[PDB]
Amino acid sequence: FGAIAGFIENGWEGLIDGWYGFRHQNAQGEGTAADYKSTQSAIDQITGKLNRLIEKTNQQFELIDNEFNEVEKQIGNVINWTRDSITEVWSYNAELLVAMENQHTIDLADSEMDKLYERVKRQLRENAEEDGTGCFEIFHKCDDDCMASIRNNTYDHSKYREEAMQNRIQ
Amino acid sequence: NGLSGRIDFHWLMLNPNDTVTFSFNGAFIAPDRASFLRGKSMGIQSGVQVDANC
Ligand SMILES: *[C@@H]1O[C@H](CO)[C@@H](O)[C@H](O)[C@H]1NC(C)=O
Image (cartoon, rainbow over all chains, first blue to last red):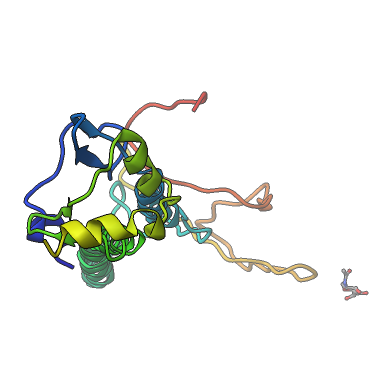
């Protein structure tokens, strides 16, 4: 999707308290916040895959060979043919199941990144523009208490609507 | 074991409500008691020790 390792240049090693977080700046300073939903929905998926593969089987199988009193040779080259070909199958699915469930895991991080980005893109509405590295250039005044209203999705667009439409075109 | 002669032991399986018959006059190693399978278990092989608390 282009988010992680696309147009965001990088990630933030200080964000202990989430996978995903906020980081703003105004006339006060800079602070590194976090986002619970976006972090938590992703945690729900990594451990969902986990709870699948733990599901084992209820089919039991007996020891059919013998490594003390050995069985016959014309049959060993057939059992060592079926077993050494079942070995080659589950070594193919673990080659494919493990290779895929990891392939499908990183992309759940670019769709949870275009889902937090195209939402703040809709609360702000027609009040900010996007520069390049993945930020929203605010041209009005928004302090520590105003930013936290975009965080918990209580920000109102018609509340600062006429200021940013007067500092963006000018 | 100091012996050169051998004893080859055979077996068959007698279904419930049936019989077995031997006719002979020599070289016979007789059976005194016949086993009866008790139920379900599992046999394996290993060359190591056991553990019971796990
Ligand atoms: C066994 O055989 C006898 C006679 O052959 C018969 O009466 C009986 O029903 C059979 N079955 C059992 C369980 O004894």
